[PDB]
Image (cartoon, grey):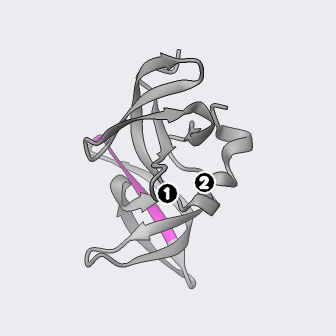
Amino acid sequence: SFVGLRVVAKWSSNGYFYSGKITRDVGAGKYKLLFDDGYECDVLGKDILLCDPIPLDTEVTALSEDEYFSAGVVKGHRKESGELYYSIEKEGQRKWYKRMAVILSLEQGNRLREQYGLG
């Protein structure tokens, strides 16, 4: 089963995909998500990506500490102390981001559904 897996799943009300874990198989292609912020919703398998971590060379949206957002490209993954960090390149410069600071826009997550989606 997919229960217990880390995924990146769409939040339908804004179209963005967020990291979380499947907690239940609701049936018929639907799954219960527990997002990493503690929000929970049912999500269709087609809107769930099996990528823990989000892949190298993927376009993502990085969250900066003052509620700004920007696109960047994943160039690294690191483990430090049981936690995942992403190295994100924007305009030739790389910066590190914690897992919750990296999300996918609708257009960024849709690109991945073929290879990673649970549809």
Percent coordinates x, y for residue 11 in the rendering = 45, 49
Percent coordinates x, y for residue 41 in the rendering = 38, 36
The residue furthest bottom is 91
Q: Is residue 104 left or right of residue 113?
A: left
In space, the residues marked 2 and 1 are separated at their CA atoms by 8 Å
Q: Are marks 2 and 1 in contact (CB under 8 Å)?
A: yes
Q: Name the disc covering residue 84, or none.
A: none
- Return the residue at label 2: 109
**Residue positioned 46% across, 19% down in the render:** 26
Q: Considering only vertical position in the picture, is 1 above or below 8?
A: above
Q: Which residues are magenta?
A: 82-88
Q: Amino acid type of disc 2? A: Gly
Q: Quadrant for residue 49, please give it.
A: top right
Mark 2 surroundings: few (<14), some (14-19) or many (≥20) residues within 10 A:
many
Q: Considering only vertical position in the picture, is 93 above or below 9?
A: below
Q: For the C terminus, which image quadrant?
A: top right
**Residue positioned 42% across, 52% down in the render:** 78
Q: Amino acid type of disc 1? A: Tyr
Number of numbered discs visible in the structure rendering: 2
- Return the residue at label 1: 16
Q: Quadrant for residue 113, please give it.
A: top right
Q: Is residue 118 left or right of residue 100?
A: right
Q: Overall secondary structure of the magenta stretch? A: strand
**Residue positioned 31% across, 43% down in the render:** 36
Q: Considering only vertical position in the picture, is 45 above or below 78?
A: above
